[PDB]
Structures are given as structure tokens and as C-alpha cells.
Amino acid sequence: MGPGFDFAQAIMKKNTVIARTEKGEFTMLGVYDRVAVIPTHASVGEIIYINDVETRVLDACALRDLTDTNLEITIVKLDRNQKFRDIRHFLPRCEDDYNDAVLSVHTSKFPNMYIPVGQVTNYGFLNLGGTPTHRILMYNFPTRAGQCGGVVTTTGKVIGIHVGGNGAQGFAAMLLHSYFTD
Image 1 (cartoon, helix red, strand yellow):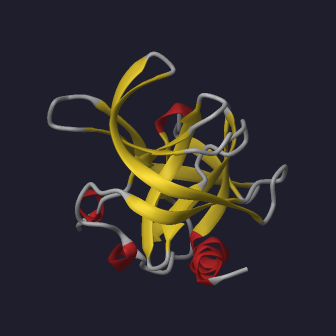
Image 2 (cartoon, helix red, strand yellow):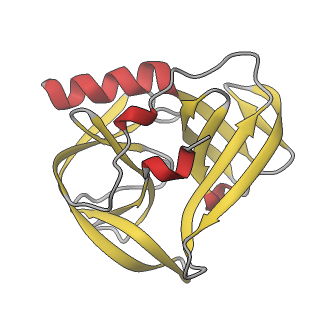
């Protein structure tokens, strides 16, 4: 509908795959080369399905901050025959709040889904399904099951991935440039 949705659609079309684990189907954001991200609660193993193709997992790392607190981000390196467009220059360097964000999902259940979630708060600490979690972004939209792994963007920034909700608010794990230096 506008330049927020334009940037979101550009990321979805080139930089997402459908990831299936034993815990279900997730939006997965490809960041560069064969490196992607997914919520840690997807419980990535030695094998994962990518767009319904059996794929070896070359490495998987559940990130934690230097307080040793969950960040709910798993960085995955896929045994895929094709690289992702490098989008690391669209990642924020620092924790921040944002205006006018879009949450975008693409699964078998929710294809081509885009949600204007509005203002995003640097919320910080959240008890997420019983796990103390840091670097949480919050938006005031009643997000539903099936949205986990959804990409949170503003015009020109990829800021987070959706990791849960309380029925009234939705929560994303921050993406920071420093996660993906090589």
C-alpha cells in the first residue's frame, strides 16, 4: 500500500524461505551467503526442511547476551546450493525504538501476509514462555500462532523477528549488525 510495505515486500520476495522443524513451519529470514535466522523455540536439529527440501544444517547457534541471558535468535548455516542476497547493511547497529513498522509472514497457512503494527518499543526484559529474554521489541497488535519468525521492518531497516505475543501485544527479538560480522 505505501513505502513501508514496499521495503517489506522486497525483503520477503528475495530473503525468506519456509523452514519446517519438528516444532512446525516458520518464516525464516536469510541474511547473507547460506546464513539465516529463526526463533530458538523452533528447536533446529541436524536436518531441516527449506521450501519442502530436506537440508543439512552445517551449524546452528542459539544466541545469548554477555549476561548469559536468552536472546531467542538461532543463527543457522544451511547446506543449500544458493546464496541469499546480502542484506546485512539493512540491520541496525544499536538497540532502538522505531515508528511505523510492518510484520511480514510467509508460510503454507499465511502466504503473502503483511501487518502494519505501528510504533515499536525497545521493551528489553521479557519472561517469554517462562524464559528470561533480553533485547525484546514490543508492538501493540494481537499477533497469533503461525506468525513466529515473521520479519519486522521499517523503510530501509530489518529490525527483528517475531517470537511471541500475549493476545494484545507482540514481541520480536532484535536483529543487530554485530550478530552477522564474518
